[PDB]
Image (cartoon, rainbow over the protein chains, first blue to last red):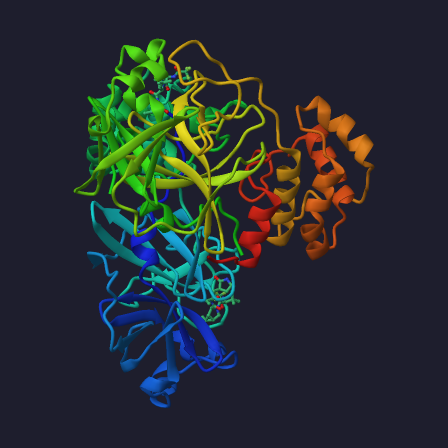
Amino acid sequence: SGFRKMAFPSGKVEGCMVQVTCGTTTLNGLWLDDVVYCPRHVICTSEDMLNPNYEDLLIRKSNHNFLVQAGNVQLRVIGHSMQNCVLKLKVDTANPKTPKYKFVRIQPGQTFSVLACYNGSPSGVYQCAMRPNFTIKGSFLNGSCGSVGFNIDYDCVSFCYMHHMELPTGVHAGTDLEGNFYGPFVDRQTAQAAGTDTTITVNVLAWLYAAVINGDRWFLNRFTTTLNDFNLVAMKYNYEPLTQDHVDILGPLSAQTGIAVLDMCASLKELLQNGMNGRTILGSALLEDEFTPFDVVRQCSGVTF
Amino acid sequence: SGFRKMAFPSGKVEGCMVQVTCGTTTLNGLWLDDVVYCPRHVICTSEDMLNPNYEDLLIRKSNHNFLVQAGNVQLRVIGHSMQNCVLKLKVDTANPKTPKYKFVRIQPGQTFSVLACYNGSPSGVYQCAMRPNFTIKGSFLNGSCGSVGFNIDYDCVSFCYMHHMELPTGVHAGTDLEGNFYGPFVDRQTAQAAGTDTTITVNVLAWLYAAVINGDRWFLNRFTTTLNDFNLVAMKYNYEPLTQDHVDILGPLSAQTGIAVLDMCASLKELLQNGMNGRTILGSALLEDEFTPFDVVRQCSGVTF
Ligand SMILES: *C(C)[C@H](C[C@@H]1CCNC1=O)NC(=O)[C@@H]1[C@@H]2[C@H](CN1C(=O)[C@@H](NC(=O)C(F)(F)F)C(C)(C)C)C2(C)C
Ligand SMILES: *C(C)[C@H](C[C@@H]1CCNC1=O)NC(=O)[C@@H]1[C@@H]2[C@H](CN1C(=O)[C@@H](NC(=O)C(F)(F)F)C(C)(C)C)C2(C)C
């Protein structure tokens, strides 16, 4: 028993982290096969980042301008190209620790483990949910760019996030591994703000199922509801509309606990209208929406990798 | 910016996890050099665990009764010995992924990363604080025993916890890597309960410093206090007495923020007497005590490994 925010084991990703230095700017890169992926603002000076012309900056750089270091070993750059907001550096050495991997673009509401890195060295790992406003509530300092987010399916590492920038509210924005930003953000040091966020309803329900599985059942009421009714009450509290796809995705948890999704919706409806009355659910005084239905099943069934 | 519960990168520990099977019982083991460490109740049947005589059970086992598997490779056991509640299995192969490591017995209030494992395979990683009652608020299922807790200092992995059992309240208890349990618990399936826990005061203060560093300063009041006065107010709320050693340990954070420890104690004194008034600190509606002063510095300064 027990339910904890749980990151994937980072070993497979730790073996892919390198340091990328261009001039005086240093950040992290992902070394997969003979290609190093890193944010393209590695080629910017502190002045360029205010309004950079990345295509122009990349002209004046040759392969030798990019210092790639895996540990103490320098990786010789034999090619460079820009794909959206990511820079692809071809190196003369294929990473022998390359895991089976994919590049995926996750959807809002899905979670992933972030391996925070500095100077190509892993610092720590934590879980993040892609917020509906396409930000993540991460912990990133100077030099953390290039740190990647990932999920692990058996032996396959699905990279889905590379860190680029921090927004005024302290939240963070980045790109997929193809360099496409999540959300309407750009890799320029200019006025940008995250849109108004919303609560990932399906994840709250998943978390309530986790609570029941772990013996925390005080919030279960006698009632049921309809998908239409619940969504009208949840809309007021800035909850995403619960779709039938979300109901279907919760099926496994509903079947395991014997609590219909719409019965759990009634309990959440009451929690949203009446509050928690000073009580906790899984030790939390707030409703948690950063656990996907998969995260709950994975943790309550012990899926390994 | 941003402050998150952050685990150490688990790669160095993932390379040491093996599966240990004795008869029908399977759990995890730590493979360091040519020795596999695992809980001794691997040698118990479901019946033995109610009142096991481990010394007796170990008589009837020979080296070949212990099936150790690193991945698909079986490690041949060439020796076995029992140290307290841990079993040491000598194998004919030294783990080539053995990191620089130590065995340490952490103190109550210190944190460590847990690598949850099943069948010798890492499932996930999360941070845990050794509670004053010598339990941890973990997430463990059947077959999770042998999962270890650790800290990483540069390149040295300090193993400090091996999981053994779960207590009635859903909290968890285990041993150091020498087999000595944390707390008054025994590896027997019998009536055992965790003592009344207490709040790790120094960690709350560290967490309040983290809040200030991250711009959350609404709780800072104009007052100071004395170590004696604060401790008398904090005692009522089940807070550990704050020692001068704790004040000294907070020095780095006090110096970085320019807020004296006793000034922060006054702010915590007010938070304990008046509550948070529906507000959050670092997104939390409760005061967090699972962040050590080191954890805060490590995360707010970007210490890597
Ligand atoms: C990557 C190394 C670094 C990570 C951030 C530094 C502190 N915390 C982080 O997450 N990214 C940057 O420095 C990016 C880069 C330059 C400016 N920048 C920012 O993150 C800045 N934010 C913004 O400009 C915005 F729009 F998000 F508000 C700032 C946090 C440094 C002010 C690039 C876009 C090239
Ligand atoms: C290790 C494989 C396993 C981990 C627990 C199973 C579920 N969650 C866990 O953390 N440990 C055990 O099964 C230990 C073993 C047997 C009984 N046991 C327990 O954890 C049991 N708890 C207790 O007896 C006590 F005292 F903590 F309440 C129980 C949770 C299975 C009932 C040993 C002590 C040999």
